Length: 20
Image (tube, rainbow, N blue to C red; front, top):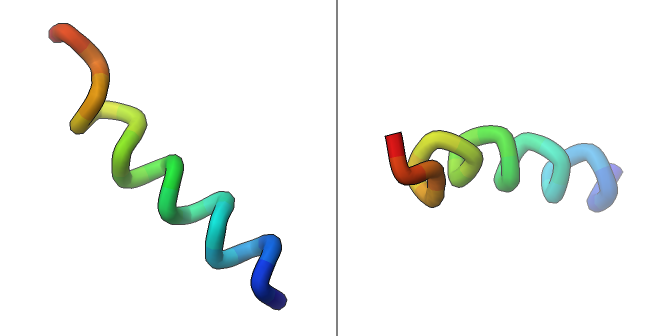
């Protein structure tokens, strides 16, 4: 269950870290 939560955390930070 903890693994899944980490997968969604990166999904939200994917565009937050992208440079456009």
